[PDB]
Length: 319
Length: 316
Image 1 (cartoon, helix red, strand yellow):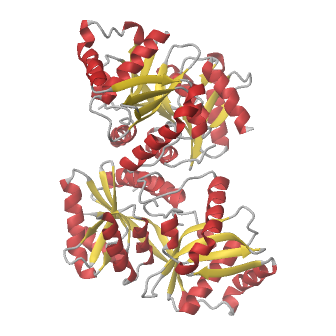
Image 2: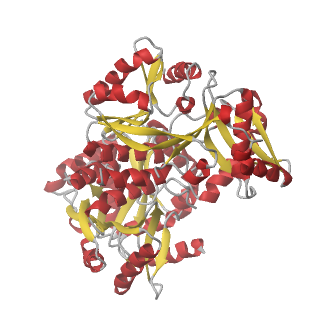
Image 3: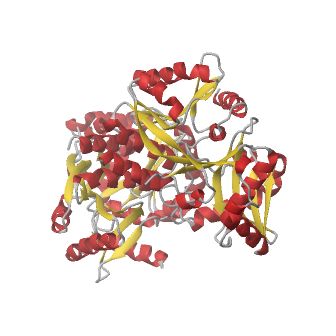
């Protein structure tokens, strides 16, 4: 069944390094396993495109056959094949299958082993941490088993945030506030006056190579400096627990037509959890991600289908 | 206030001919009024685009200044101005502001004064009505004061449809199942046995020149021929009530711009019947357009429109 597929895929996710592969847990993406069952591709189907989300996940030795399987399955259904936000490691597999790569933007990766808050280089970030604390802000990472005790309070903040921004939930490359999904991972929370004013679900794996956040929401009353406070706090917590890196997520960049399209796509989806300049304060290394498609014409058409998958898309699994 | 603007826009809608102007009731679109307050443009803001939905609505004398007001307002905000699904009549107002037009598709308009069901030309459809009735189908237009009595059952049929098609509600050019919105207009309902198996909200005005539907949802258990039964029953009802036409909505028509428009059509104009289905009612086909400053902006604007309809604003 689909539920059994998601469970198995999640078990694969926890034994590998990519933290965003935890997005399979939302259950809104189709899953295709390799012959061995040790690797998988997660994807969406929209209009005339089959769109895989990021890289294949799991045992790397299965990636060449999986990529080919996906491209052939899309061709067999009369659809174009495309990979959305793949890493440099996957470009060779994609080129072997006849695809071209277009840079979509860059992930801001913070090396937590060199993130020294008591050093002169991050003095401002340190000062913001103590200033947030004087304003009455406190931080905690709530482990999976304790999330039920704050569920009602998380739900209120999430609804308040949706209403305040007059916006709706997303899908595919972004998670949504679905109780079972929120219950499956740790939650970083921010409190003021004994009340949760912000939260972010943490995506981690058992290898500790990388951690990232998915949703990030603040009550309209969260004080100035709450984003600095939350991020600095998350990075310090992760550093002390032994994670090597923290992924701040995609940022737009700092071939002409498709160039305009990529530029507006960046602004449309890569600014929900801080602007590029905000991410730059943590001194991240910038790693590129790509859209892999057959031709340049298909690029724009595939990105449009991807836009629907993210903006509207499937209902998904609901409790 | 926004609620106050929605109310005023609605009063303007009920006194004019375009039935789809009733979408302003969803409260998800910004409203810009003309100086006299007898006309308005309803629009959305997404990315670097301001997208007007359809034509200005109301007193046609105010249309030229409104089109200009809208384009200027968007220029002042640093955004491209675009008009989504405008009629042939508005192309000159847009051309005066430097916008060219691209055909999006065509509306199927059925002349209800010449819709003769028990006449030779509609033999097939007449037989689908009798077959539907034999299969135990009944039809009824529920007025506003009675919608509360079937709201719980409509909610279940709507929720079952979303789950069955594994889809989400839309916005902007399409309404959603939101109680206050569904309660504001009549609902055409289809029953099999003693149970609602399909529904569609009816959009009408006091002029009776046109009616159309917005949502159209059939439970997975609805029998084969339910669509024929509902549309034929809707048309007979509207014809007997004195309506001149029934708008079946946009349909696809069918070089990089052409591909975009083609995939756009399949993505949004096939929710309430395929082109072939609408054609059986012998409608006159009327073109609708996308107006933008130039060719390059067309795909960009249409992408912003796609977000506005697929995701978009939470609304009221």
